[PDB]
Length: 11
Image 1: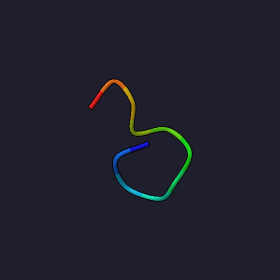
Image 2: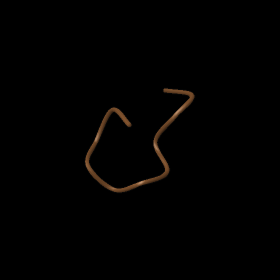
Image 3: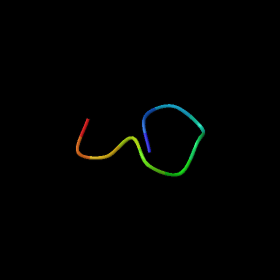
């Protein structure tokens, strides 16, 4: 997770 909110991968 490259942001905090649990959705951002694959980044």
